[PDB]
Image 1: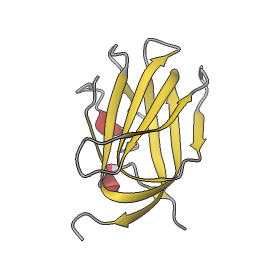
Image 2: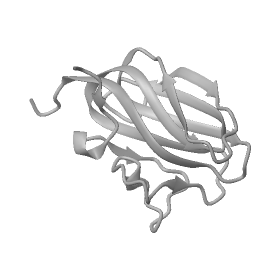
Image 3: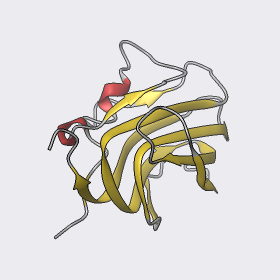
Image 4: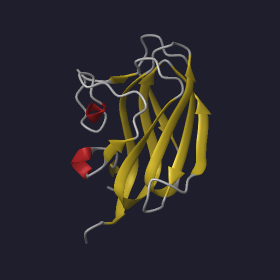
Length: 143
C-alpha cells in the first residue's frame, strides 16, 4: 500500500557520478539488492554519488542500511538535468560496528535525482549495503 522501493534499477532508477566506483565491487549492486554485494570506497573522501530516478517520485522515507558512515550529506534535485540541487537532510550516522542499522529517515519530498555526499566516516572505508526510498511514482518519464 504505497511506499515501494523507488531506489532500485528494477524500478528504473540507476546510479551516476560515483566518485569511487569499483568494477568488481559494482555500485550496480546498490540498486540490485543482493546481500553478497555492497559498495565500499577505495579511499575517496568525500564520497558522493547521484541516484537517477528518471521520473517524478514522491519520497516519504529514506531507508538506509550502511556501515561506518559518519556524516551523510543528503542533497536532492527535482530538475531534468544533473544540476539544480537543494540540501535536503544532512544527518550524522551512529558508528555501527557489526550492527545492521536500518535508518528510517522520515523525509517528505519529490525528487528526480538524489546526491548522497558522505563527507567523512568513523572508518576510512565506508560501505553502503542497501538503500531504498519509500514512496510512490507520480510521473512516468515516457508516459
